[PDB]
Image (cartoon, rainbow over all chains, first blue to last red):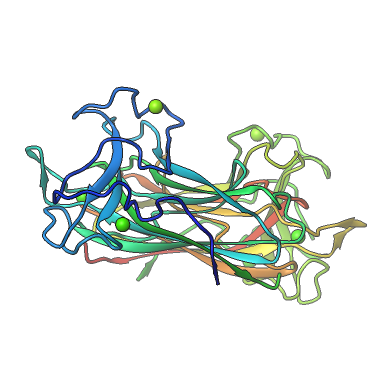
Length: 200
Length: 198
Ligand SMILES: [Ca+2]
Ligand SMILES: [Ca+2]
Ligand SMILES: [Ca+2]
Ligand SMILES: [Ca+2]
Ligand SMILES: [Mg+2]
Ligand SMILES: [Mg+2]
């Protein structure tokens, strides 16, 4: 299977030193996906936020360290359940090829324990999408159950046929918080995308 | 794992011979958020209904995965115009510490219908609902060859912290209109609940 390059795929940029420290800017190489205006221009302690978090072996939020490297990404939404969806996305240089099976793998984290006076109990869910152009080709929404303080790996698969209308369009990836529970933060790590031949 | 009743789950109503209806299958509702499916339908409008699929069908390598009949969802509009399909609200309600398994066969109709080729596919999406909310979904994780049905599984665990407990379960079977020929079929809808370890 051939690995397709992804920018800051492990959220290892930026490098952090302080255990359980969290940035508050979009991870480099990723874009804030925010179709419903849930992530404000000015981010404070009490707003929706995304960024990266140093998750080591003695994390207050996870039983084991980051699935990959030191860092995971997080998408937190402060608004009420049902207000919309937001996350991270990235357009790749790779393009959709026919007779090709695409496998998009991502680790999803459900932070647990305690944060800023209040429990991290609960989980907003997740959605992971493979795109070509602005089309969602394939997606998984909440097929995996993720325990508090745990990470689980989800897989999104798609085969492009010779008749596909999206051949040659740039691939993309979206990591989404669908805001379907509180505490409404969901973490991501170790984004991988492979292509391999498929007979159709 | 206890089975959760669905109305006309295999699309066996109405009984057919030789072979298709153009009205919403009984037990199900047209899902049409983007207004692509008229109340008044013809041969050539966007459409849904039930199809008799025997062992020597023009459209499939094999007979219906279950019984005699399958459901179809056909959209006449251009690729990217929106989504539509079939949905059903169940009597059962979402329950905590429970794993739900939604199983549906997806079909890629092949061959030809009265001279018109069925080559190509619009994709699919299957959704498990509570009230108005999509709890869990699969869009196009499976590849379905022309003239084939494949089984997809959508799973969801409802925790004690879920905000949708007590809301009526539902099922949506969607044509996302990502290709032509823009017909996709479904059969043998199943839903079970079983105890989960949260
Ligand atoms: Ca990492
Ligand atoms: Ca949590
Ligand atoms: Ca049937
Ligand atoms: Ca077809
Ligand atoms: Mg914004
Ligand atoms: Mg309508």
